[PDB]
Amino acid sequence: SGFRKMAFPSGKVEGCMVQVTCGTTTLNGLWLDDVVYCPRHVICTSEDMLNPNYEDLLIRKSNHNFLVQAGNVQLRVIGHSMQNCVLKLKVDTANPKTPKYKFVRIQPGQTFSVLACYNGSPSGVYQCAMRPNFTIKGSFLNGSCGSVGFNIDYDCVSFCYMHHMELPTGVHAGTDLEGNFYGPFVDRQTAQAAGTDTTITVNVLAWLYAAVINGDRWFLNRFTTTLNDFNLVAMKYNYEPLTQDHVDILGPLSAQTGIAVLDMCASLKELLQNGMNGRTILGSALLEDEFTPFDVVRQCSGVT
Amino acid sequence: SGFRKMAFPSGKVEGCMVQVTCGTTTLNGLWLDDVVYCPRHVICTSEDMLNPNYEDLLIRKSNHNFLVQAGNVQLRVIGHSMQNCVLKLKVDTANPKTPKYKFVRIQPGQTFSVLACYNGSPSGVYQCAMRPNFTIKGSFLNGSCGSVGFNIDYDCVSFCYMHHMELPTGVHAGTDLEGNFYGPFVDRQTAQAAGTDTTITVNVLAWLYAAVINGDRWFLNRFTTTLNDFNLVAMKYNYEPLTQDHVDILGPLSAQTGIAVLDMCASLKELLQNGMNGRTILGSALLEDEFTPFDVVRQCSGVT
Ligand SMILES: O=C(Cc1cccc(Cl)c1)Nc1cncc2nc[nH]c12
Ligand SMILES: O=C(Cc1cccc(Cl)c1)Nc1cncc2nc[nH]c12
Image (cartoon, rainbow over all chains, first blue to last red; front, side, top):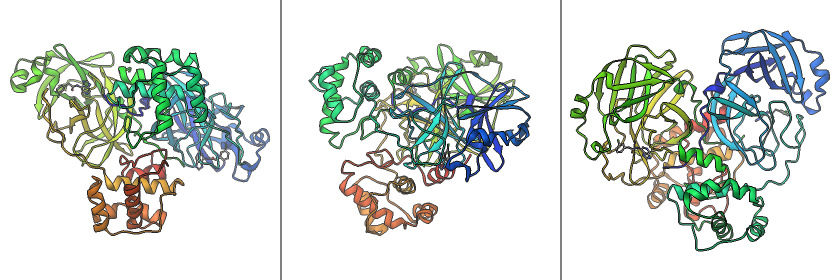
């Protein structure tokens, strides 16, 4: 029992972290096989960041200008290329600690672990969700760029995020491992709208099921609702509309607890309309949306 | 910017996890040098757990009865001894992945990361605090026993906790790495009082400073208080009395923000007496006490 915001064990990812320096800028890189991936803004100075012409800036750089250090050892760079907002630095040595891996583009509302790094060295690990507006509410300081987000399935690491930027609002933006930003963001020092965010309804319902499994049941009521009725409430409270696809993904939790998804929707409707009344659910005084139905089953079943 | 419940990177600890089986019981062990440490209740059957005579139960076991597997390879057990509530199994091979380490007994109110494991395999990592009543509110299932808590300082892992038991209340109890339980607990299947818990005041104040550093400032007021006045409020709200030692440890955060510790105490006093009024601080609708002043400085400075 107990329910925590659990991250994946970070060991497989720690073994891939390197420091990349270009000119006066240092950030993190990810070394997989004989390629090091890092944000392309490693080639910029502070003056360049207002409106960088990355193509022109990269033309002034040669392989020897990219200093890549894996712990205390230097990697020899034999090639460089820009793919969208990432640089791929070909090195002459395959990372001996390369785990089985994939590059995936996650959907908004999905979760992943972040290994925050500085100077190629891991500082900490935390779990978070990709917001419906494609930002992440992480914990990142100057130098964290190049830190990655990932999920693990047995021995395979699926990398889904590389950190690039902090918006003036203090939220975070980054790319998939092919360098494509999640959301409308561009890698420039300009104010950029993130746009309206919403609460991840299917994740809140999953967390309510986790609460019932772990004994927090005070919010269960004698009511039920329909998808249409519930979605009128979700609209008022800035929650994502619940679809049958979301109801289907909640099937395993509904079967385990014996609580029909629409009955749990009625509990959620009552919590939205009345608040918590000073009570808590799984140590939280707000409705949590950073656990997917898969995360709940994984944590409640002890998947390694 | 941003503030997360960040755990230490778990890689150094993942390299020490092994599966220990004795008879029909399987749990986790920690392999450091040529010793494997695990909860002594690995020698019990379910019938034994009501009131185990560990000395007698261990006498019926020989080195060959302890099956220790590091991933897929078997370790040869050449000695066994019980130290308080842990078993130390001497093996013929030093763990090649043994990091620099220490065994420490942490104080209540301090924090640490847990690497939850099942069958010797890591499932997840999370940060938590040792409650003032010596329990931890973890996320652990049957088979998680032997999972450890730890802190990292540069390249040295200080192990402070080994998981042993879940109380009937759903909270967790365990030992230091010398097998001494934190708190009054015994390794038996009996209902056991945890006793009154309190909120870790110095940690709440540290988190309020983290909130100010990250821009959440709505709770700052025009008031101040004294240690005596604040402690009358702490008493009413089941908070630990604040001492000058706690004020001293908050010095760096008070210097960084320019907010005197007693002025932050007045903000905390007002939040305790009036609640959050439906507002949040660092994404929380309650006063968080699982970040120490050291954790706040570490996260806000990017220590690796
Ligand atoms: O935002 C940047 C640098 C940057 C500026 C403009 C565009 C780009 Cl792509 C990158 N670094 C950063 C990241 N995360 C957190 C931080 N806190 C301070 N700086 C942080
Ligand atoms: O509590 C036990 C077994 C046990 C019983 C009596 C005394 C001792 Cl020392 C150990 N295992 C366990 C731990 N954490 C979480 C769990 N959820 C289910 N079982 C869990």
